[PDB]
Image (tube, coloured by chain):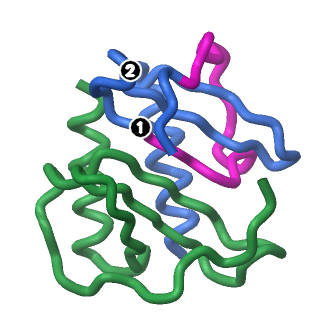
Chain colours: A green, B blue
Amino acid sequence: KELRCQCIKTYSKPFHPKFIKELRVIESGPHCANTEIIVKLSDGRELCLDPKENWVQRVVEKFLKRAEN
Amino acid sequence: KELRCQCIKTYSKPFHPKFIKELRVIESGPHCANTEIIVKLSDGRELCLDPKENWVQRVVEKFLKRAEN
């Protein structure tokens, strides 16, 4: 339940939110100096995304609007 | 990695986003007919939230804005 940082790199190419099926956002703290965004893709693969990127914020917002329907 | 629905009930009292340290959003699919929002609180407890509630959408948005700083 208590892991260190989970992301070794972040994916830098924008993509459409339809390809996300799960989102995890882990705020920075004693376990990891960076906030981490981990997404599970439609096919089960996992990717980390940079929370400071405008396109990442937009993709997350769009995923949330959809999952909430 | 493949669980059924993870939420037995959702917490119905609004609260301040400062008390969230992790957010998971799991879109509905074959594993669970409902989209689920699971938050880890500052002290490690877990709560599920109803994604259709306006206050929940607002708390999530605020958490994201903060974690992204």
Residue toward you, A60 or B53 = A60
Q: Residue furthest front?
A: B2
Mark 2: secondary structure: loop
Whether label 1 touches label 2, CB < 8 Å: yes
- Of all chains, the one bearing label 2 is B
Indicate whether A61 appears above or below B51: below
B7 with respect to B51 (left or right) = right
Q: Residue A57 appears at what percent x and percent y?
A: 32, 65
- Label 2 is placed on what type of residue? Cys
Indicate whether A22 appears above or below B58: below
Residue at the spot of label 1:
B26
> Reading the chain from its start, which is encountered first: label 1 or label 2?
1
Q: Residue A26 appears at what percent x and percent y?
A: 61, 62
In which quadrant will I find the C terminus of chain B? bottom right
Mark 1: secondary structure: strand
Taking the magenta stretch, the answer to whether it contains residue B22 is yes
Taking the magenta stretch, the answer to whether it contains residue A6 is no
Indicate whether B5 appears above or below B19: above
Residue toward you, B18 or A11 = A11
B3 with respect to A20 (left or right) = right
Residue at the spot of label 2:
B32
Badge number at residue A11: none
Where residue B39 sits, quadrant-wise, is top right
Where residue A21 sits, quadrant-wise, is top left
For image coordinates 79% across by 74% down, the residue present is: A31
- Label 1 is placed on what type of residue? Ile
Segment colored magenta: B6-25
For image coordinates 53% across by 79% down, the residue present is: A7
- Of all chains, the one bearing label 1 is B
